[PDB]
Image: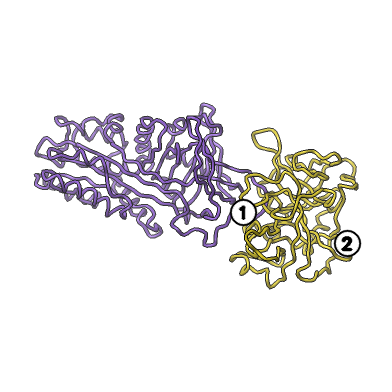
Amino acid sequence: VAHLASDFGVRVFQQVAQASKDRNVVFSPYGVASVLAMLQLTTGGETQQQIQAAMGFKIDDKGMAPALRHLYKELMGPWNKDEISTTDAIFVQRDLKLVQGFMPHFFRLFRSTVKQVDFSEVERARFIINDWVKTHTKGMISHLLGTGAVDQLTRLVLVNALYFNGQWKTPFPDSSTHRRLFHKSDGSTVSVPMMAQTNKFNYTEFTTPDGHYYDILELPYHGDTLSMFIAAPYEKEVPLSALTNILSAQLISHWKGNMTRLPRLLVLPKFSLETEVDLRKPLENLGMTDMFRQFQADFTSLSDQEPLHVALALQKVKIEVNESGTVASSSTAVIVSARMAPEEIIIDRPFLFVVRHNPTGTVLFMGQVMEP
Amino acid sequence: IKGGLFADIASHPWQAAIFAKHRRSPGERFLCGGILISSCWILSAAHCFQERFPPHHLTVILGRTYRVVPGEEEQKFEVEKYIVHKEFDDDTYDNDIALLQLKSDSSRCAQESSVVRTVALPPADLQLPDWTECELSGYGKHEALSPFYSERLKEAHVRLYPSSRCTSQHLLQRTVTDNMLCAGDTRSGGPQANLHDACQGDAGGPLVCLNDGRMTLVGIISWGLGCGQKDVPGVYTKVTNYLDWIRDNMR
């Protein structure tokens, strides 16, 4: 059910990944899919059948809408200590003539509404949008550069944003964070700050079909509800997009399967990443061309009055890795504790990560960390 | 070993190094300290083996000053077998003690010399006077954050804290049992302040104190919130609680 959406969103990530060279990407495979599924309702004929193709389901089919809702339900959040924050929002022109019985049916499936603004008066289409995000992402995301391209002929526009911050089952002691030589892909080397902790961690070694090994490692968040999975190659010449483009929702499950809980000295770099994505090409790469075309976009289920096309569609993600929120050594956490010499695991190469909703296997975040 | 000073194995001839073979690469990496109590046996810490290597992966090295240079008169052993305490707790480190039997032919493994010799096990009726000074030895890190482990054996001196000062109150809320024992450096702290403590990689090593004018094994390095902190003692395995056990696990 929810693996379908995640895996779709992975595909979305692949497209951006390959376009973004050796650059910091962060992305939400849930985020992307949760709005496309929405926009699915608001489309017709081949425009729809295009995006249902890519996704692999009809939000229209039985139980399928309930699912997402109920997922969203969990994410926010009595256990979620202002840690995540989602939003999905579609906007359209204020004064328009929509089909009879749709916007209610749409509320029925998603329980949200489709937001109606005035694009003619551009100054505060922009504000309105950048402050929808602002409100729903607890201010952690405010601006949104891609909205610049909003004009007055711009009439249908789609947004998705999430801000995630840690809160580890086992946090790193602040005491022990030291600057450390990270090596970038090209060759160079940067003195980045890297937190260290000697605990017990779920680990496994994975190899792709092509003889590429990575260290896979799970760092769970409090109550084990969310996990982050880091994945870094043995030797530094191995491309990430070697794994990244066989990545999958049941791939992640494959890792947790092979994991055993082992005592290791983990060394890992703090980082803070924010990517805004223009979804057009990515989505068009998947064969979703119709939605952005003036003449050909079928939005008749919500439209009636025509044409009506997606001018702009965007995602803005922000992940933060440190140790949760200012908190720092309670002192609960501490550097070594028990005094054996353990196998180190150092993360000075570029790697990638995934954040997961372990109960449902839903893939919430993703990224290449090419340099902190 | 945080604080203290480098050493000669001859000053601590029961200290052993324990090595574990890698898992992709050829070769061993340093694992734990160990203590020669009988010719063919060594004590160590339980938690050294949380990752349950088969014995054949383990090598013990007696009589060696440098952790990676072979000593001239050293004595190297393949482990025949090892016995982790049945009720070692992998979260509180309660019952932290192991027994390694050395693989040899002839019921006679290590042999005495100026650099390899067994240390006396304490008498069961041993109760030492509080703040008694004891020593300890290890190849471990010099400070909690040091990238690498020691290039050479170090020694340290600490004093046995009294029971009242070995509760978890004095260990930042952490379980402490009648099987554990805290020693630490009771001098004035700075910093600077190089408070003698063991560190990462010293676990399994000995804590030896004078009694009857006889160097006698009192504790086994175990845990701490290391290394060398604010009158936060280093925790040890009370060796006396395990005398019957040890006996009963050599048959």
Chain ID for label 1?
A: A
Residue B169 picture location, percent across and down: 61, 69
Q: Residue furthest bottom?
A: B164
Q: Quadrant of residue B68?
A: top right
Viewed as shown, does residue A69 lie left or right of B35? left
Q: How packed is label 1: few (under 14 Cα within 10 Å), some, or many (20 or more)? A: many
Q: Which residue is mark 2?
A: B214
Residue B212 higher or lower than B64, as above or below: below
Numbered disc 1: secondary structure? loop
Tally of marks? 2
Q: Position of residue A8 (x, y in %)?
A: 35, 37
Quadrant of res A14? top left
Q: Give the purple chain's letter.
A: A
> x%, y% of residue A98?
11, 44
The residue that appears at 22% across and 35% down in the rendered structure is A48
Relative horizontal placement of residue B140, taking residue B211 as reference (left or right): left
Identify the residue position indicated by label 1 in the image: A336
Please determine if labels 2 and 1 lie on a single subunit. Answer: no
User: Coloured how?
Assistant: by chain
Q: Residues within 10 Å of mark 2 (few under 14, many from 20)?
A: few
Q: Colour of chain B?
A: yellow
Residue B4's tag is none
The front one of A247 and A117 is A117
What's the residue at 79%, 43% (across, down)? Answer: B61
User: Gap between marks 2 and 1, in whole Å?
Assistant: 33 Å
Amino acid marked by disc 1:
Val
The three-letter code of the residue at mark 2 reads Arg
Tag 2 subunit: B
In the image, A121 versus B121, the foreground residue is: A121
